[PDB]
Each structure stands twice: as C-alpha cells, then as structure tokens.
Length: 209
Image (spheres, rainbow, N blue to C red):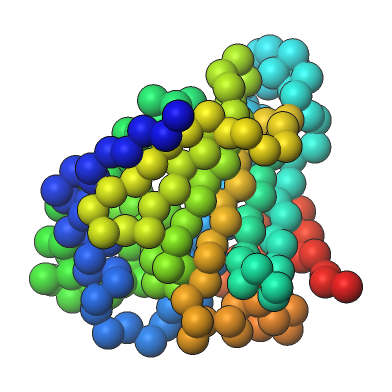
C-alpha cells in the first residue's frame, strides 16, 4: 500500500532550483545530510537524559556512510531520533515553506546554494547529486516507514517491508550517472575532512569488498 502525495508548491520550487541551477560545488550535499544526522542524534541524546528507556532501541549514537558502486548508491545512516509518518509527510520534519521563502529571498540578496542548510532545508540538497532519494526511518513507538521521491512534484510513503532498523534514519541517494565520484573512498574522506571535520558523533566510512 503506497500513498502518493504532491509536494507543496514552495518545496517543488526549491527542488526545481536545486536540480536546474548551474552550480558546480555539489559536494556540500554531504555536509548537509551529516548536519541533519547530527541534529537527530542530539535530539535522541537530550530526550534520553530524562528517559533512558528511549535508548532501548539502541544506545550507540553514530553516523555511517555506506557507498555501493554496484547499486550506485550512497547511504547516510544515523541512529538519531527518527521520524514519524506525519513528520515524513510534513517535509521530513523541516520548516520547508518558511525556510524556502527565506532562502529564496537570501539568494536574491547575495547568498548562494551552499547556504541552503542555514534555512532548514538542507535535506533537499541531496538532489544536487541524486536522481532519486529514499528515506527509511524508525521513531520509537511508531512503525518503520519509507519515503521516496525522484522529484517531479511528488513523493511516496509506505510502511517499510525491509529489515527492521532499531531507531533512526537512513538516507539512500541513488546517484546521477555523472556523480559517481561520491562513491569513491578518497573523495568521501576528503569532503568529510573539508566540511564535517569536527562534529559531536563518530562517522564510520564503510569500505567495499
């Protein structure tokens, strides 16, 4: 049972800008997704201070980066607070309508695309390098859901059939044909060091057989 939804007008316009604007500095997508993961880890850490049972679904707070050259995917996994179905549908828990409006105003006034994270809509920078994005998420006391979009004005949400994750979010980037550099170990290391060197959680970069 798959539900298909239209993006709000503002988000469709944001995604179009990201996909259609000439902007060579695409590597900032990774900092934005790592930033989102770190925020989600902060949330479950703070909630667990007054209720330790919220870590019954996993005590380790970390970020994994998983390239797969066969599938042409880069996956960013975190064991953060996860998202409910309502969150997923409501623009993956972002303030995307107001954030987009502010971002667009900033772009008119001298900002550039790399500042997208400042406005709370950094997730959508995935579409700098991905033709399709899948978000698998599990919040405590909600079920596991999968969100997916290849832009074009719509997204889908279904309950996730696949392997149970304990808690957190997985963002699966199906990369565009010309963006496979982001599957290379030395390229990913370079970008993490350049933009995400000091953050509050361990990042593990998986290797491939």
